[PDB]
Length: 146
Length: 76
Length: 377
Image 1 (tube, rainbow over the protein chains, first blue to last red):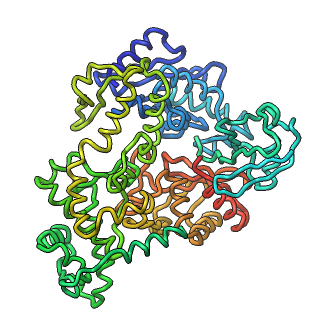
Image 2 (tube, helix red, strand yellow):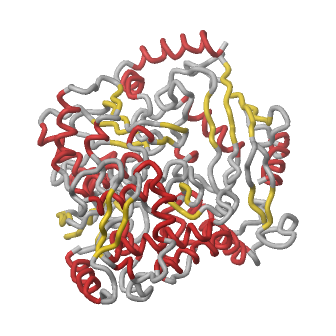
Image 3 (cartoon, chains in turn orange, cyan, brown):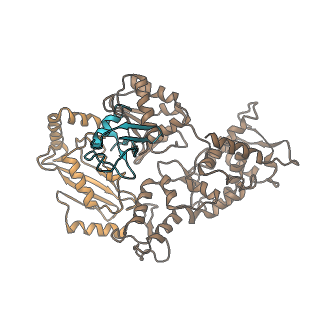
């Protein structure tokens, strides 16, 4: 896990995943914090979002726990910043790397997944009343992201 | 052409189809014999997830080939 | 199911009752200090044969004239004590699995843990012998260990799916890119120290020439190395009531059903500790049906239902109020989602169930009993 994390860390400052930057804060190497810039021409445009990448001692056999810190109005991310993303749970592989988990998250941001929701209310509003959704998401970004 | 779709419980779905049916339609047919919607279905065959964009010819799903009904329920 | 019956009775009879022993076993102790009291009593008997006597128990507290029903209770009461995670002899495999396994660091909790294990075994067998059940469940490897079976990468799937899949990957691919080393990591006091699976493992790498011998050292470590003394002391006592071989006829699943029972989920404690989000609440029509649906299921459909939704088929020792998410306490939840056509979904991490607003009780039941049965894939 040590060399794994360390090495995976240098690889970040090798090909910085565009639109985001995660890195260990403090001296603890099992607690990182990442940023993700609202994908462009998406309602989350302009804002910035903070996250918490907590590596368990079982990494990489167990997926890392990644959560949003910054509030965000999205169908697959709740008020705790919990992220319903398959590679974080069911489809995780010891070969997968953070730089890949971050971009995967930026994708979920611009192109939500309304059919495997975590927050039903939003999913619906996103399916039926799409323009409403953009209005709101855009407002939440103005409150907690900026 | 006749095939079997086995559920994880045991009960099996015998059905009628042309070798050119898009997998997506095997689901539309299963959606009337069980009520199970298509977006919550996964038909596994010999350890392979048979996409919707293909047909019964693309995977050589012939007369009597058994696929499976593994319900994609868990959410994300 | 229909078979297990044959094997059971056939098993029951094969057991024999000595002759030179009392009609019953004299047992009387206080409920509030039941552990060390049952302990000092059983573990003091000279002839381990006498425990094959009839079970006669009385509490100097809740004196009620049953004395035959107390038997069922004593076991249920001694279990919550023997198999209590916070005692230190046994612990939970995961923070959300509720299945017990020998605590490798047990010797550092009871300065004479071995004697205690021998006892928990002494009792455990005593229950099988008198057709009673113990309360709690152990990870498969515990049972395999009794059956004298090997523990393999396979056995870890039940304990920690994700860890099993990751190991299996290592098994089926080249693990030189993962940059692994022969040593897993630990925690205590927030401290994070490294531990070697073998000599200097900390240095040694996991190549494509040793990843076989690696996965071994891992399983070896996770379920065997550090608990062989205990698991052994346990069998010593378990075999002072039953011939350890008389039991090999059953398989892990049957052996579990044999001594730990099936374990039907208490439906009332459950409804009473569930929370409803997004429209649903205690009296809402759909929620009221859900529970009636639950009420009509048999012991299996329920445990199936629980697993489908919480990820585990077991329930915490202190009830449904102590349920856990992959993030800490998380009461069984039921949220409203989807059109009446869709099947109910589940998030095992938050023990949540997305139940669509069915229109007719029977409509709901046919959809739930469907998700449950044809599920787990």
